[PDB]
Amino acid sequence: AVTKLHVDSVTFVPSVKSPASSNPLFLGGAGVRGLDIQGKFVIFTVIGVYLEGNAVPSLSVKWKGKTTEELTESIPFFREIVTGAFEKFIKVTMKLPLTGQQYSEKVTENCVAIWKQLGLYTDCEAKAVEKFLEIFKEETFPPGSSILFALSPTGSLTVAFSKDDSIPETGIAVIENKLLAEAVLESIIGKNGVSPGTRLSVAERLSQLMMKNKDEKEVSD
Image 1 (cartoon, rainbow, N blue to C red):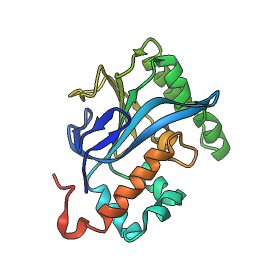
Image 2: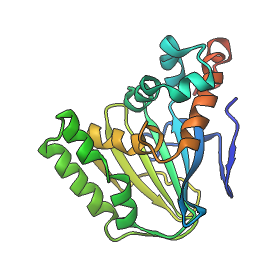
Image 3: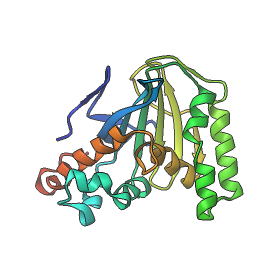
Image 4: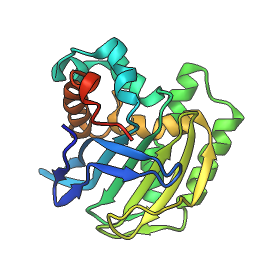
């Protein structure tokens, strides 16, 4: 069930080693981030989402048996993935050239308003966003380069970069803020996310994996 995925011209492998924990993570799903510009659907980035193996049995408790459609429309299901006490990893590969400032401002364009809406915006989050922006401030990402995000089980966000599809053995910096960490993944597969394709892909694959898990345990190690 955990096969590689070909999205646009990129190929996401079945498993990657987390630059933060060095633990293996399986390919949950992949898709593109694009938008209609003057009549043409322009693809900006190609995204892959990886999850920790223990996430399958964890999610199975409440979601085993749900169909792809049921999981795709489920706000609670994806919120459980985003806030789950397990590691998540995101590989964002550029198709179009993007500057670190453009990209970082795009990923965080809604989180502040969202946190204020929920009454959760504190100085900790303000500092986290500032740090996030500083990390990307002077970076440039040509087509083919990648931005890697590792979300720890407790909410720490590790940021790393790559010139291609390779995954570095360690990250660049870590932002210790659960809300910002979750916001990065939410911006992709959440209800207000930018990639319907990635959300659908994750739903489809997890629906199948949760009905297997038991005695197949394909996400072990």
